[PDB]
Amino acid sequence: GADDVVDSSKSFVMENFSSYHGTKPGYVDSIQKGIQKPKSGTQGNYDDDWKGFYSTDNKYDAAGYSVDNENPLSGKAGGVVKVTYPGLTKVLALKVDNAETIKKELGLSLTEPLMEQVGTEEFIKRFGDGASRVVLSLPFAEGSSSVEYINNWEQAKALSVELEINFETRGKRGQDAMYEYMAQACASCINLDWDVIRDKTKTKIESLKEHGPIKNKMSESPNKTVSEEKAKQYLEEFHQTALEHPELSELKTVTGTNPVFAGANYAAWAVNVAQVIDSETADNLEKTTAALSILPGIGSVMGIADGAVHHNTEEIVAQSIALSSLMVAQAIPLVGELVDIGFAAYNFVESIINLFQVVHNSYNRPAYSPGHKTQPFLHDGYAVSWNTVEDSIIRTGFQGESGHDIKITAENTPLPIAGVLLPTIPGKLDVNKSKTHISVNGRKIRMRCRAIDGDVTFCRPKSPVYVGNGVHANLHVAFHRSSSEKIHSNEISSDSIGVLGYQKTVDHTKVNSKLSLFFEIKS
Amino acid sequence: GADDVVDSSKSFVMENFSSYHGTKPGYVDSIQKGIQKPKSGTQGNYDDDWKGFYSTDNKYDAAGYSVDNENPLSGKAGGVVKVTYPGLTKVLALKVDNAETIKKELGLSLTEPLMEQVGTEEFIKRFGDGASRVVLSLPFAEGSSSVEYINNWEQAKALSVELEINFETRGKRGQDAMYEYMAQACASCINLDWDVIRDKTKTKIESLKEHGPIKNKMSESPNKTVSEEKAKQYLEEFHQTALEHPELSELKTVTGTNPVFAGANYAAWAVNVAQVIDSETADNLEKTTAALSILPGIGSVMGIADGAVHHNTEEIVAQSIALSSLMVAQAIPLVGELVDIGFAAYNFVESIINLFQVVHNSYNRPAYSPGHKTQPFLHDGYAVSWNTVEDSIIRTGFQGESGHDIKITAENTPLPIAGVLLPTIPGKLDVNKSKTHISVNGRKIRMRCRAIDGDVTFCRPKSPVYVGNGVHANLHVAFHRSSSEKIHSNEISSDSIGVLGYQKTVDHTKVNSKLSLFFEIKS
Ligand SMILES: Nc1ncnc2c1ncn2[C@@H]1O[C@H](CO)[C@@H](OP(=O)(O)OC[C@H]2O[C@@H](n3ccc(=O)[nH]c3=O)[C@H](O)[C@@H]2OP(=O)(O)O)[C@H]1O
Ligand SMILES: Nc1ncnc2c1ncn2[C@@H]1O[C@H](CO)[C@@H](OP(=O)(O)OC[C@H]2O[C@@H](n3ccc(=O)[nH]c3=O)[C@H](O)[C@@H]2OP(=O)(O)O)[C@H]1O
């Protein structure tokens, strides 16, 4: 019944219960006059059972609901307000978001929209625990630790509303105020001054234009349609010359080694832009942002590769954007259609500043790296992951066994799995070699394991293991503990299980493809 | 308690309960004399609680335990025997394989090895349901529908043993008898006559050697160490000439279009072999098989690409193996160390016949294709999967809602998600656009969906979505049903959800990267 849908351990009564609501440009002031079910719109939900007023415990999450709905990609963001219930409010945490289940389990009317019934006396009598009203709590989203609050429309009229932030009052370009506010969430942390980046970029685009060898490199330009193949060629040379400009120097240093950052990738990027921008698009930021957002390769100009944001100083990001701008201007005539001159310096910049902000925001948010929890590790054609979050945890402090499943497959042709590297601590974490195995399309293959140093055993499949399109494996590791003593950090040298892929005489030193699954020791 | 570890719905009592045991060369006859705990070895398990006699309900699975333990990769397989318990036997299906949990829950002694206690009168009294003995049942492996039977050593003495198959009696080369027996499992189905493939290959290797233009192409060969770069070059030309031989004609046709099957990949393969084979390895099949098994690229010679086994006639597989053999012979002198002449024609062939058999066996086994159940779809740098098996099921026949989670990330730099294609049937399967969203590192992004034909709606993220190393997304699709009528096959045009990746003007016709998640309609 009721404990199948309500999680009472995380339900509580609070006095002066507060939360946030993201508000659109046009309502930051009026919503402060009070909360009321609007006359236009879906009123909180497409589904009747879920119609009500929505808030979240996180003001940065509330902020993501503040963008003009007509231009959600590049419009103004309005603000955040904090709404508070006077007195006592019961926050009832639900284990499920299915309204038919909750009405059934909670034994309510199966007919009335659940959210109407939450605002009833009877419902508040039964679940309010003496609070003046009930608000439902659900997890905000996967990968988030916030909660979403679903308020009954009528009970919401009691909310007091105050301004958290009105982003438009900030007076910044684009969605600069919204993103600077969200960057506060992390104080590591990309906290760039976009006003400065915006200003240095302009100065740089201007200066590069005046540059004689640039003004010349441009003179070599076909200045009319040529295949991207020769447009790529003109562009790499152009890039090669612009990057010698004293104002794109630091950028010269930082993009020299990494292949993602190469001149070829800036040219591949510029060619892609010039080819998707027509005059109507070029004329509208929203549509410019809509088109730029679906192209591959933006990481080259962003300085984002391998899990890291390399271009992370206002100076270097401004150089990279200014270099990109100039090169779209060159690409437009050779591979596109429009007023090259215009777009490149204006809506191209406005729009790409916005995509930088979108991507920096994600990297500022807590996330799992490859091979952590259930995030896959993608490498050399293989995809591997802990089947579930508990598999990634090696529990300690007890005598007995555990089992841990790792999914393994590869994208296409049959790639071998040479074996696996596992941590061992005698007594506290032994490998049970009878129970450990690898299953290929259900075929169970036992392993032969051998000691190594670093308290690592190397296990190989008794028979050949290949994975690929249509062939998948489950590596099941069974650990055995003869001691009830807890594993100590000292005792463990590795924080991952290592699956070894195929062998390459990379460096003329035989090396195996390495795929890592990171674990955690607990209890 | 007890219903936390035993699954009584799948436990039963049977008269003349039968099962299979894979037996090693040396024991097919003697084990027929009766089952007895051996004096040497782990007696069924490394863990004491799990020591006992092991059997399986599947004779093809039993067959995978029959290979000489000293040369598990290429040794002889012994056989399968069927063991039967006279009278009544209780098969007790366990929900868990953790012996401490089962002893606790089943309230048994925490001290005695569980499997000793299963063979006790008291234990048989309590769980035998009137059977003369209890056997424990566990799922054989992930991706398998077999079961594993764990028999108490002492109760196992009552088993009657009969010969299923003695593979050695078959008189075949390598592990031909074992693999032909396992191929019976599927009657689609690779059921090759390896005797024929073995014979045609020899004939072909011999004939190619005599071939004048080949004997000549060989005359162009540096016949001494040259970098793989020039060894690759000699090899592609050599391949290009050998494939013109009338005996490798069909092969000429079938490998002409697919890039995996190209002459360059046969040369990349031959170079990899010549470089990992030394004289000692070349002299031992086991070690030859151990080294060949960890190299990438075998799919080129196998004719295996995109989930399919293309070389599936004895004639074409013999041509491909004969061509591969000849080319290792050429590669050895240029990039390796040994008696090129020897290995290539002998242990190289014996060994690669075995890897073909290993890989054909996997493709003969039931498996999930990319994007089915929780198998990921790997494409264009992206990895996507249904988070759990239930997510992949769209249930029908009721009024209400469902939610379905799809994991999304990409291997490195930030790749965009343009939107998603979802099936719609009015009333029976509507998209609830309030509840449907995509979460990027916890950032919840709503969608705007638009109709299409084929009862498909196209939904785009309100804001830009990029995934990559360190940035992952959860696409949560919420479906709503206003009708309690079941979805009919007629009504649904698609069997997958389509995630759309970045855009490419591939064909000079703008195309999006397509990632598919296949669903099933039930109830
Ligand atoms: N005086 C007012 N009293 C009440 N509402 C007012 C008032 N003034 C303006 N509003 C707006 O009215 C709508 C419902 O409250 C909300 O905006 P939306 O643009 O429809 O908001 C878009 C969606 O965001 C949801 N959402 C918004 C912000 C948030 O923090 N959490 C959340 O989930 C909304 O429920 C809405 O859902 P539905 O579109 O599915 O109805 C809200 O901002
Ligand atoms: N007369 C006999 N009575 C009993 N055993 C005899 C007899 N003659 C030979 N044996 C062998 O003795 C061992 C235990 O029964 C088995 O072989 P293994 O090579 O140790 O077998 C290798 C492993 O395969 C397991 N296994 C084998 C076949 C099978 O179908 N299922 C399964 O899980 C075994 O329990 C064994 O585990 P442990 O190594 O972890 O002990 C078995 O084939």
Image: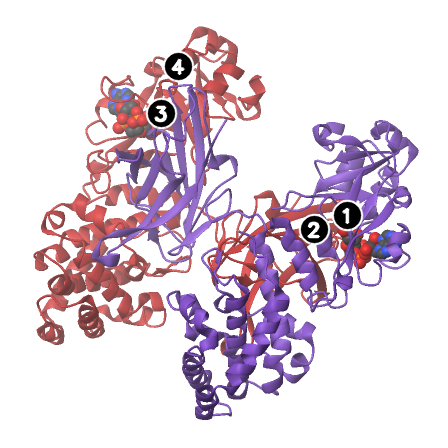
Chain colours: A purple, B red
Q: Which residue is drawn at 18% across and 57% down?
A: B275
Q: Is residue A348 something that shows in the picture?
A: yes
User: Which circle, 3 or 1, is nearer the viewer?
Assistant: 1
**Residue wearing tag 4:** B113
**Residue wearing tag 2:** A61
Tell me if label 2 and label 1 are in contact, CB under 8 Å: yes
Work out whether B164 lies above or below B519.
above
Name the amino acid, label 1: Tyr
Give how far apart the Cα atoms at labels 4 and 3 are. 16 Å
Split into 4 quadrants, where in the image is the N terminus of chain A?
A: top right
Name the amino acid, label 3: Tyr
**The label number, if any, that marks residue B41 in the structure image:** none
User: Which circle, 3 or 2, is nearer the viewer?
Assistant: 2
Q: In which quarter of the image is ligand 1?
A: bottom right
Determine whether the beta carbon of the residue marked 3 sits less than 8 angstroms from the nearest atom of ligand 2: yes
User: Which circle, 4 or 1, is nearer the viewer?
Assistant: 1
Which secondary structure lies at badge 4?
loop
Residue B309 spot, x, y in % from top left: 36, 58
Residue B139 spot, x, y in % from top left: 46, 31
Task: Tell me the chain of label 4.
Answer: B
Task: Tell me the chain of label 1.
Answer: A
Determine whether the beta carbon of the residue marked 2 sits less than 8 angstroms from the nearest atom of ligand 1: yes
Q: Which residue is drawn at 20% across and 39% down?
A: B75
Give how far apart the Cα atoms at labels 3 and 2 are. 55 Å
Determine whether the beta carbon of the residue marked 1 sits less than 8 angstroms from the nearest atom of ligand 1: yes
Give how far apart the Cα atoms at labels 4 and 2 are. 54 Å
* Camera-nearest residue between B12 and A337: A337
